[PDB]
Amino acid sequence: GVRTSPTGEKVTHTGQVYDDEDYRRVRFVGRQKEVNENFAIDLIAEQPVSQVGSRVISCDGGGGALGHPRVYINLDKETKTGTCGYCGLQFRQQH
Amino acid sequence: LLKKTTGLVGLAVCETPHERLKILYTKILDVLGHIPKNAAYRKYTEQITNEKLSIVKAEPDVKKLEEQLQGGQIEEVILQAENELSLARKMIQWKPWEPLVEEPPASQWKWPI
Amino acid sequence: SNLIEVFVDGQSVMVEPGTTVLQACEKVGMQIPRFCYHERLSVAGNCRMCLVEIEKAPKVVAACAMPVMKGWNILTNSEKTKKAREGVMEFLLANHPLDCPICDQGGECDLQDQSMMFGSDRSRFLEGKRAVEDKNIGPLVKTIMTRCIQCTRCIRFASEIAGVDDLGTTGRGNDMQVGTYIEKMFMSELSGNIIDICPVGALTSKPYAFTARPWETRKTESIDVMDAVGSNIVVSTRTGEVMRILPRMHEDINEEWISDKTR
Amino acid sequence: TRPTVRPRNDVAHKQLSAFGEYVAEILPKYVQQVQVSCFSELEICIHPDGVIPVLTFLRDHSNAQFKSLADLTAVDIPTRQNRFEIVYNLLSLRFNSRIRVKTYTDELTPVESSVSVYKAANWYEREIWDMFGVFFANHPDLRRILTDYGFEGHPFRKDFPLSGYVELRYDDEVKRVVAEPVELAQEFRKFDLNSPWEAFPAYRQPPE
Amino acid sequence: EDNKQFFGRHRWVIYTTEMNGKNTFWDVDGSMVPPEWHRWLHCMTDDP
Amino acid sequence: TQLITVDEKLDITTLTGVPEEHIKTRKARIFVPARNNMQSGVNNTKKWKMEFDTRERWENPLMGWASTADPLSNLVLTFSTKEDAIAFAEKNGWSYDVEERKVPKPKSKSYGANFSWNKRTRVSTK
Amino acid sequence: TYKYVNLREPSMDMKSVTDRAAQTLLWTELIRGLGMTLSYLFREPATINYPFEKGPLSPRFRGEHALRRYPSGEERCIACKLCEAVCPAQAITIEAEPRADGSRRTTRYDIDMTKCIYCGFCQEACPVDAIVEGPNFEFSTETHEELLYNKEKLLNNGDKWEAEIAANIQADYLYR
Amino acid sequence: EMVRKCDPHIGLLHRGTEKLIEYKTYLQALPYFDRLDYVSMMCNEQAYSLAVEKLLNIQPPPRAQWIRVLFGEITRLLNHIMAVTTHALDIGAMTPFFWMFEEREKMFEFYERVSGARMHAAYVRPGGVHQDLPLGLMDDIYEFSKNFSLRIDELEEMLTNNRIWRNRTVDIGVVTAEDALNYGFSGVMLRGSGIQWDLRKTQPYDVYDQVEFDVPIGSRGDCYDRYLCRVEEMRQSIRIISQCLNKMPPGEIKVDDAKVSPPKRAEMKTSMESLIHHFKLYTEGYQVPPGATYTAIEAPKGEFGVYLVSDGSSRPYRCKIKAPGFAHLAGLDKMSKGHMLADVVAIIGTQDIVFGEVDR
Amino acid sequence: TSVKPIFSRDMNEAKRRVRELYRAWYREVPNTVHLFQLDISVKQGRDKVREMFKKNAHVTDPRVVDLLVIKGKMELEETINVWKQRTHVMRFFHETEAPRPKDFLSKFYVGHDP
Amino acid sequence: ASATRLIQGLRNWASGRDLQAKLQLRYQEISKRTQPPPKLPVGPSHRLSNNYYCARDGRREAMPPSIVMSSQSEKKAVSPAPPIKRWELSQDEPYL
Ligand code: SF4
Ligand code: SF4
Ligand code: SF4
Ligand code: SF4
Ligand code: FES
Ligand SMILES: [K+]
Ligand SMILES: [Zn+2]
């Protein structure tokens, strides 16, 4: 979800944009500002919450040794989903 | 049999190695007699020089003398005898059997610091 | 003087009666590994990382708690001391989570450092680990309780120094959880110091969360000005920006604590 | 301890200990320590007044014959009052051996040049002048060898900073490469890496 | 491909005359190869 | 004779190539570094350290990095004792200030004191 | 266990002396050298037709840096700063914060490609395979600061080259 | 025409390498050694790795030792091709440069397949090597080595019996053996003068005591004997590579002490101890025990040594780099007296001088 | 408090050597201006040599002034021989460096440093 | 490899060698660019038992250097090692 400042400048996924009175916009004059349009905070929120039937799940990000270190997530809160601190995939105990 | 070259560049062949070795060993013992008796350089160098001179007096051959002196060619054994002679002539001047000139400072050789 | 003579690795050292084995090793300049012992907390003895061999004694003793007797030869580097350290470290790392990149304690972790120093270099644990529900004890102390090693420095600090008596252990066995058992918020005036004494990233600083990392920080020793105590602090910076404020030890002022405002 | 641990050599350890006793009692006027490391390397710590009598000994004596000067080195140690530690690495081809002859100096006391023993030293200690500021007496042509021609200071001292004090750039006003005080667009990030737990109990120092 | 040519000549690209709006009839470029063919052309794999 | 008598104070500032601005305006600090309270290890509190006063760090206009103009900004020297550090500072013409070593005082530890009869040092839990 | 290069005495019979003088006067070894050069004239050369043909590379190749994402679009980097701790040239500059969902992510990830020594210690220090040094070597610029990459350029190199980086890591992760 | 004096001024590539090493860890200091003798990359890697492993009191696995000797002899081929062909290129023979840099291109493909970089691999590490051989690499090393003898034969066709090549090398750069030893020469600079000294024979490292090779000995100490010594060292390197390809053992490629060598990436993502050890090795690095070693190898230019001093920390306190070319270029002044200006460039060619190792 | 000398037994031999080094530099300055085709005057270069000598005029140790004579002779040998270029000679004249603030008020204006 | 037999014979004659036997250009004899996945073996410390690290710790068995002489009979003069053995001339190819 990229947006645009009043100066016409794209705001990055970090939130950086130069101010109106900031001289450092002159580096983009006649050139471009390279932002990445694939925001990971948007793409991870599109994922479905995975319903599992255990009390503690494991997550390695998929792909085995191609993902992240394997972590175990406790799913005892029925208020909040159990979110992987590495990959951001989130889990819910189905009962 | 007159070995054609020593194999080392700038090291000529000695035609009469035994007489040259006897002259150099007796000259090392002559210079080394000027050192005091308590000096370990005198005792150690007299020991090795008398052993080498005994071996040179014991062997007529050049090849077997090279195999039992155990110093490579006979010409670099002659070179080593000359270096030992020059060293002992310097050791007369330096007098290193004397006690230590200065103790090092208190943590001069302490590693790790 | 009633000083008795004890031996650490054969070296003689004169100690006051009632000296623990850890303090006798500390007098000859040797630091025993520990997780629950803290020199300003009460002695718990519940991590077993300090187990050292007394010679002519067929049992390792908890050096954090055991008083010395006269003439003990403490063997800090013997074989069964090292086997005790490696075994206890393996049990500490069995259910411990692989969070070292996403953990703020990384680079300043006692569990990492004395896993490198006193433990084995690989795992034999072929099972699944535990995962513990995170607690909410305030907007200051981030709580990730899977990383907890149940050393009870929380509870001894909050009981003895902060005078709170609200942290505790619930349950029994491998399900023993350190928490408050209820949705209760641990806000003392000294509630930040549990981030200092926790040897793992189970309790971390929520304002300092994810922002820096201890090897790239410049440690400027300075003074607090928030009160008139004059608490000695470390301002740690990174690339010309203040990252956090830690305590310095001064025995006469702030012993090794600071208030939450200072922190 | 078989597969991953380096196998200890006891024979060369014993031989280097015996030869260190030999060198120490032949030359007790200068020899201050003799030590053999666990990986079997012999170090002869001598007094700086005996650089030449020791090194001419080991080059010329018929039980030493250290005919090659492999490397000559200085090490700055600022916690010593003689902060520089001059290190001679010697190779005896005849006995297939290596020896280390270590001595010391501070900023001001000269060391005698060993070019009359090993001509190989002619640049090394010259490098030691350029990098550490250890003056060598009776060196044939002592000058700088590695730094720039107008360079002030001696870089491999540990009180000298990593980047220098001056940087260079072409200035177009003066049509010339010029020196200015160094200003980095990004400072070198000093990392505090040392763990606070002791790694090696064998090397523990006695406390105060 | 030409597997009878020697290793280095055996795979090649003819670049297009127009890519992303730019006339590349003469101004062909080594970075005009997309990444799925970049393994094949640089012989990082046997499979196109 | 071959030894002379020099009774002047040891000062090598004209030899080290340091410019004058980073001799007389810098304040060397000589101190045993305080223990990181994140850890219980004390191996980093063993040797004395000499650092300098931190000068300006500012933002790179292009990238946002920490730019500096201080050559001595990363210079940390390590000394076995305090007096070696003081002698190295006085030898180089550095104005220094020394903080004394803060040693932790020996505490009185007793496990049975957690379970006393009449004292306040009973622990309420374990 | 040793041999003597150049320890041959030439033979002194009239056959060998006349052979050496015919070599001297009639230039036999020079015609040998001309013949070896003429033998290379009629060989197929080793020249590849760059840029239409490319030099062969391996999947271990260390080229242009890129930041990878998961197969959900979430970026792999969790701001642990191991790559900038291991970086031998201090080419990596990382700043982080918790972002709006509490995830541990970077706000700054700079690689100076003019400090970088292209040794790949960052990709092998990375615990999540986030920073990788990809297959691209054709990224010469006309300006110095176009090689001063920030997080946007690195995530765009990941999005640009992921179809190839995933296959190189597929072919080489079992050696790692 | 005569050269009375030759004063080399160096420092034009002085980069303060070994002051930069004091502020980096041991793993971070390893790629500096690729860039010293930058036609002998893995040999300098091997010298520094042997130095660190000697201070660490650990040893590499046998397969890593055979890979080190294999790639060190591939490196010796690289360095002597560079040496011989640029020494001929300065004198004027420009063509075997082009003939032998294609074989050198194939050996850079071997480096790129084993490490991912054609020159500065950072591959030989303290504790073993970084990564195992990719499957099919040793077959291609076999197909290179089987044909490389004909390439040496046609180089030696183009130079050895050539009268113009002999007239530029035979009376030139004569060093007596005693002056070669007294000037700190090493390698071919000794063995051209008849000295029977090679560190792979006399003070052998990793598995050189298990390979069978000859040592070419010069007889006159000139540029021509040193040329023939380098050609025959390429021959004997092909012999060693044949033996290493025949005798490569199975097993691991790092030391299985995981407090020195990093664990595998599959087990770093599974085990707690492996992730802790991966973390601490790639941030702090391993602590090396305190002490000082002087570890030397027979690099293809001569004795390449490291005097490495650890103070106990995970960073080197001191790392002096003894390079052969430093003492060789020091002896350039004696080697060129009584010769001419076109002979000094041949002397500079036959002392294989790369100024990265001269200047550090 | 008894140390080994470098060249001088006392301060007087050291001042003899300092004096002879100043003589040699004073003689060499016109040759230096001519062959490096410097655009300074000879008087300006002799003033710079006077400044570089009088910077060190506070040193009361014979060993330190012996080393200063040694380093000055090395600079002189690098100037007599064309080993320095024009740039290394002109680095004594800090031309591209803007004059720094010297008083308190302007250093207060420009930044934080004393 | 694609050269005609006339050019092949000319090239072999001008070099004086059989050049087609050892071609410096590479063809289908080299390894496949795509390989099957490996199963690399583990080291000797990948054992679930009898694998305490205190019994295979290389860095902790490093000792401080043993001080032989320090400033706090008719015994044999020693060398640092026995004298080096004279090398044998090569039986393979001595050039003699
Ligand atoms: S607490 Fe320590 S061992 Fe556990 S994840 Fe954090 S850094 Fe790693
Ligand atoms: S949260 Fe930390 S201090 Fe509290 S009991 Fe657990 S490990 Fe100990
Ligand atoms: S390849 Fe090496 S130098 Fe480049 S960013 Fe990665 S770790 Fe740093
Ligand atoms: S790229 Fe990898 S190593 Fe670097 S900070 Fe991100 S997760 Fe850590
Ligand atoms: S320290 Fe004694 S058991 Fe925790
Ligand atoms: K904590
Ligand atoms: Zn996950």
Image: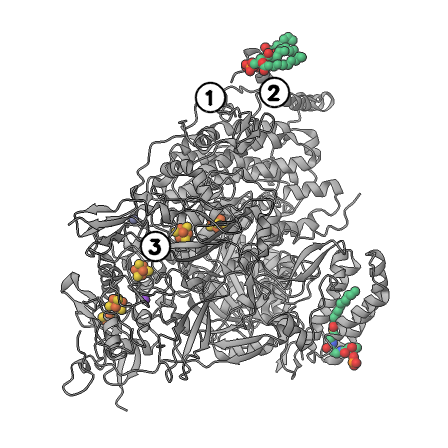
Vertical arrangement, residue B26 with respect to residue A63, above or below: below
Distance from disc 3 to disc 2, alpha carbons, whole Å, reads 71 Å
Q: Amino acid at mark 2?
A: Ser
Counting from the top left corner in percent of width and height, residue D35 is at 45, 66
Circle 1: element type:
loop
The residue mark sitting in front, 3 or 1, is 3
Residue at image mark 3: G101
- Is the C-beta separation of discs 3 and 2 under 8 Å? no
Left or right of residue G37, residue E21 in this image: left
Disc 1: CA contacts within 10 A as few (<14), some (14-19) or many (>=20): few
Pinpoint residue G62: horizontal percent, then vertical percent. 47, 41
Residue B75, visible in the rendered structure: no
Question: Residue C261 occupies which quadrant of the picture?
Answer: bottom left
Q: Which residue is drawn at the image coordinates 68% and 60% (left, top)?
A: D144
Q: Which mark is residue J74?
A: none
Give x and y (percent) for residue C179: 21, 67
Task: Give the side of residue H32 with respect to residue J33, left or right.
Answer: right
Label 3's element?
A: loop
Q: Amino acid at mark 1?
A: Glu
Extreme residue in the bottom direction: C1
Q: Give me the disc on residue G39.
A: 2
